[PDB]
Image (cartoon, rainbow, N blue to C red):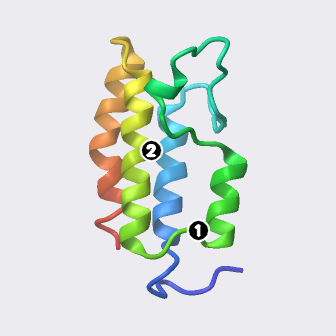
Amino acid sequence: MSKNERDTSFNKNGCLVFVSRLWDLDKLGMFHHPVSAEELPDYHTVIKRPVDLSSIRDGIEKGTYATDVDVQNDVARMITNALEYNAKGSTWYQEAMSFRKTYLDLARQSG
């Protein structure tokens, strides 16, 4: 269980803030899967870099990251992509954009 508050390699804080904020943004709740091409024919353009639960869970578990810097950058990119795809105008758009203001902060300021 766990490893350490900080070993200059694994930033558990980033994962907690990421999943925590992600759950809030995704009103549907428990949302963590790649978009279907059938509905997103331009997924390659909108989300050049898709995100999946198995891919993310496997990445952190394996240690794909390198440090607080790598984790921070990854999270930032994920947020940008999500916003680019969720960019509509409804309440979800504002909520996502508003949370994004603290999404990166929580995944960088704590570390």
Instruction: State how far apart marks 2 and 1 are (Cα).
Output: 15 Å
Q: Earlier in the sequence, mark 2 or mark 1?
A: 1
Residue at 52 percent of width and 60 percent of height: 16
Residue topped by disc 2: 78
Question: Which image quarter holds the C terminus?
Answer: bottom left
Residue at 57 percent of width and 14 percent of height: 41
In the picture shown, does residue 46 fall above or below 81? above
Q: Amino acid at mark 1?
A: Thr
User: Is 26 in front, or is 80?
Assistant: 80
The image shows residue 18 at horizontal and vertical percentages of 48, 52
Q: Amino acid at mark 2?
A: Met
User: For the residue labelled by badge 1, is the local secondary structure a helix, a strand or a loop?
Assistant: loop
User: Is 36 in front, or is 94?
Assistant: 36
Q: Viewed as shown, does residue 31 lie left or right of 106? A: right
Task: Please tell me in which quadrant of the rendered image residue 34 appears.
Answer: top right
Residue at 47 percent of width and 68 percent of height: 13
User: Is 80 in front, or is 95?
Assistant: 80
Q: Viewed as shown, does residue 108 lie left or right of 8? A: left
The image shows residue 52 at horizontal and vertical percentages of 65, 43
User: For the residue labelled by badge 2, is the local secondary structure a helix, a strand or a loop?
Assistant: helix
Q: Viewed as shown, does residue 91 lie left or right of 66? A: left
Question: Which image quarter holds the N terminus?
Answer: bottom right
Task: Please tell me in which quadrant of the rendered image residue 94 appears.
Answer: top left
Residue 53 image label: none
In the picture shown, does residue 4 fall above or below 100? below
The image shows residue 54 at horizontal and vertical percentages of 72, 50
Residue at 33 percent of width and 12 percent of height: 89
Residue 64 image label: 1
